[PDB]
Image 1 (cartoon, rainbow over the protein chains, first blue to last red):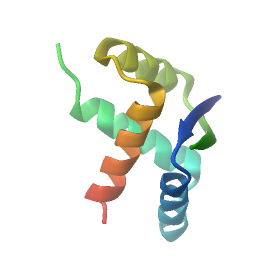
Image 2: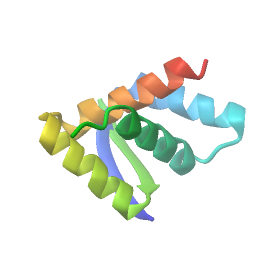
Image 3: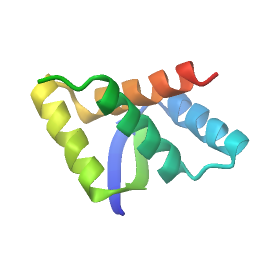
Image 4: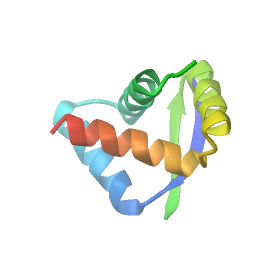
Length: 45
Length: 43
């Protein structure tokens, strides 16, 4: 795993952490899933 | 806005970065949309 750094709205970051807490997910796992799901959804040729 | 630091698979990071290049997005815009869409769909 490598370090990934990006600017986001502070309230988005809070919503993501809240969501992780409710599903007992690590941030790394949740964020990875959200990114993979978006890339999958938006893939084109 | 604020810095968000998280550890991810290196190959996913590269994939994300390549995608942002091809779609002419900032990483901030891309990541924000992926997270927002994920949260939106799953609530």
